[PDB]
Amino acid sequence: SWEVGCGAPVPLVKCDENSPYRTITGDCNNRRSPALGAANRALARWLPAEYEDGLALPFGWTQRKTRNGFRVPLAREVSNKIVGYLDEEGVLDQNRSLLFMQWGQIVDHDLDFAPETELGSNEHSKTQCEEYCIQGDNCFPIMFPKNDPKLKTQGKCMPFFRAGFVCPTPPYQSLAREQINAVTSFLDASLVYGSEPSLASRLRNLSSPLGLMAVNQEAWDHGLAYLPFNNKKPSPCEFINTTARVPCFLAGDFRASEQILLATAHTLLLREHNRLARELKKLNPHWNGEKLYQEARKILGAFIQIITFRDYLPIVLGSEMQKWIPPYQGYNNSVDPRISNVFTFAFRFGHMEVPSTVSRLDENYQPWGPEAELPLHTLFFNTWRIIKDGGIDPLVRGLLAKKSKLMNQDKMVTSELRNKLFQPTHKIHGFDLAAINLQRCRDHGMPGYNSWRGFCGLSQPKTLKGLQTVLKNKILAKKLMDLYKTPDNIDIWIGGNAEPMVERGRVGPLLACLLGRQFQQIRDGDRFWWENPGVFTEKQRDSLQKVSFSRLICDNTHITKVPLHAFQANNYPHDFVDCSTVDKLDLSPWASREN
Ligand code: HEM
Ligand SMILES: *[C@@H]1O[C@H](CO)[C@@H](O[C@@H]2O[C@H](CO)[C@@H](O[C@H]3O[C@H](CO)[C@@H](O)[C@H](O)[C@@H]3O)[C@H](O)[C@H]2NC(C)=O)[C@H](O)[C@H]1NC(C)=O
Ligand SMILES: *[C@@H]1O[C@H](CO)[C@@H](O[C@@H]2O[C@H](CO)[C@@H](O[C@H]3O[C@H](CO)[C@@H](O)[C@H](O)[C@@H]3O)[C@H](O)[C@H]2NC(C)=O)[C@H](O)[C@H]1NC(C)=O
Ligand SMILES: *[C@@H]1O[C@H](CO)[C@@H](O[C@@H]2O[C@H](CO)[C@@H](O)[C@H](O)[C@H]2NC(C)=O)[C@H](O)[C@H]1NC(C)=O
Ligand SMILES: *[C@@H]1O[C@H](CO)[C@@H](O[C@@H]2O[C@H](CO)[C@@H](O)[C@H](O)[C@H]2NC(C)=O)[C@H](O)[C@H]1NC(C)=O
Ligand SMILES: O=C(NO)c1ccccc1O
Ligand SMILES: [Ca+2]
């Protein structure tokens, strides 16, 4: 009896073993072990958790306790001394479009979500944490350094609440603390449809037999849909501009409105589901609502899987791609498809790819208006700019014509995210995503940098000179040493991202290994992987591999000129072709004949 028992945050259902459709919760994917990969279960552990008291307290909680003999540096100090920079000039990725960054966030949200602990609204807890900066229970504050300008301007700390854990929610005492993944581990478009039956149903248009998703009724985009507004007040979206009073959107995932470009991608996907569903109603007039919904949903999930694995991963892993993700051999029921705890930190390499501004372009791809280029921080939880400032068409063009930020050892995360992050729960544009990531690593009980190097079969630097050789950077390796005093204590998020990029990729050795294993596993352990014989017919497969993000844009926006390879850097007008030159998805293979 391994630690086999606990199972509390989870459901009630039966499995229909011959259903051709995925469940909403992920349950029933694996036949021998039904709960594998399902939502609201613990993140898998590739290595034992490392807590200060061996079970739940994070390192840095008890100032008198050390980690391998040394105090762990304050998250915000590492942020200031290492992660920050002032000059945005020369920081853009010359061969990756803004879409490269945006797709990563989409894939990250489809796979993992560890929500913070709630326990109390009409509670002085939210007060005692933000107002007095008192560590205790789920309040684990990010204290400011001496000499930090936020001390003079914001307070003594940044509130931070520990992530939820399986089993309960109130105090737990025996086995080690395991964080929750609130979404399904399979790449299945759960960010569009939801991971709970509760929300999946609410997102659907059930008053009509067409299998469509509910759309906004207050607002339209030149005859195209917007996601419906969300029903919870107070909403962070109307707070950022109490005059416009425009709420956040309602999507399969709760993070949809964190930033305008993410909300934009969610809208494109919502539209494709409806486009697909009314297009299927046309070929199969007899199919009912449920059939239309499931069938369009199945297609959309295949689309996300194809673009991710054919177009996105090859340019993230580069030459390491083949090393971790060999060609598909078919479904393997012995593979654990669960997303690991460390993956949720390794996938955060994307934060260093976010630029400081977002632009809106007009039909010739020229600046759209007088204030076309805006600072990223004014777009956090901003939905009013979409509904009241031109729709998504100007934003989508920016995604195609602008570049991502390139990871740079001297310029890691932009100040828009490092000093001005807005949290849905608080009211200042003054948080630090980098310090939060570091703090969260400790909160999740992550092993140090060298434990992961070993796990991936990579050398493990013990000295400064050793760290210089791995990082190939003398001064970085030595800021790192002055703060951490041993490479063993380096938090994985900063350690992984500090490594030089592999050839043709955008991450280093350690990250390539961690990312590559995870993706190989969610592909091989998915009974509904699009290439698995029997999921789709041979003819449906020939049709599916013609999808492209470019075509998705053409069919769901009023944009008529798009690049052929949307993820690489493309210059207008030279790299842009006419939408009619672009491959469509041929849905005829989905036509049925029941007589
Ligand atoms: C403007 C762009 C982005 C913003 C503003 C943003 C913001 C955030 C915030 C606030 C968190 C919660 C952190 C915590 O409490 O621990 C988070 C988590 C995360 N982000 Fe980002 N993010 C952005 C882009 C990206 C991109 C491009 C990727 C990948 C390519 C990515 C991957 C992740 C992952 C994996 C998590 C942890 C998710 C979980 O499992 O709970 N993010 N982000
Ligand atoms: C900017 O990035 C581009 C995409 O990453 C890159 O083009 C890619 O170059 C690789 C070189 O390995 C080629 O990869 C493809 O090679 C053949 C196609 O001829 C296929 O059999 C392989 O499976 C593989 O997909 C491609 O030619 C191309 N990749 C794609 C997806 O189009 C550019 O070279 C980069 N531009 C600059 C200036 O560096
Ligand atoms: C909060 O949202 C407000 C409304 O969405 C926004 O004000 C709006 O934006 C500007 C005001 O600065 C005006 O837009 C422009 O409209 C035409 C372009 O078609 C121009 O010819 C006008 O001169 C004008 O500049 C809108 O009139 C204005 N709308 C309202 C109702 O005031 C605020 O700027 C937002 N406030 C913040 C702090 O973000
Ligand atoms: C659910 O679907 C119905 C029908 O497709 C939507 O209503 C139609 O679409 C628009 C807006 O209402 C108009 O063309 C007609 O008024 C409707 N036609 C029919 C035949 O009803 C409705 O908007 C959808 N509801 C939600 C919440 O998305
Ligand atoms: C299905 O996946 C399993 C688990 O990943 C694979 O297991 C391999 O088999 C060896 C022994 O034969 C195990 O020690 C390892 O777990 C795996 N090999 C290596 C090199 O790590 C298994 O090979 C897969 N089965 C099929 C039929 O492909
Ligand atoms: O944008 C986010 N993640 O990419 C995000 C936003 C708010 C809360 C948690 C999150 O992970
Ligand atoms: Ca999923």
Image: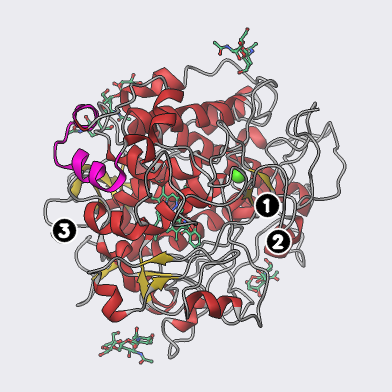
First along the sequence among labels 3 and 1: 3
Q: Amino acid at mark 1?
A: Ser
Q: Position of residue 213 (x, y in %)?
A: 65, 60
**What range is drawn magenta here?**
465-485
**What residue would you read off at disc 3?**
88
276 magenta-colored: no
Q: Is residue 136 above or below residue 402?
A: below
- Secondary element type, mark 1: loop
Q: Residues within 10 Å of mark 2 (few under 14, many from 20)?
A: some
Tell me, for residue 195, which label it has, or none: 1
- Secondary element type, mark 2: helix
Residue at image x 70%, y 24%? Answer: 534
- Secondary element type, mark 3: loop
Q: Amino acid at mark 3?
A: Glu
Residue at image x 49%, y 27%? Answer: 517
Q: Are marks 2 and 1 in contact (CB under 8 Å)?
A: yes
Tell me, for residue 199, which label it has, or none: 2
Q: Position of residue 390 (x, y in %)?
A: 36, 73
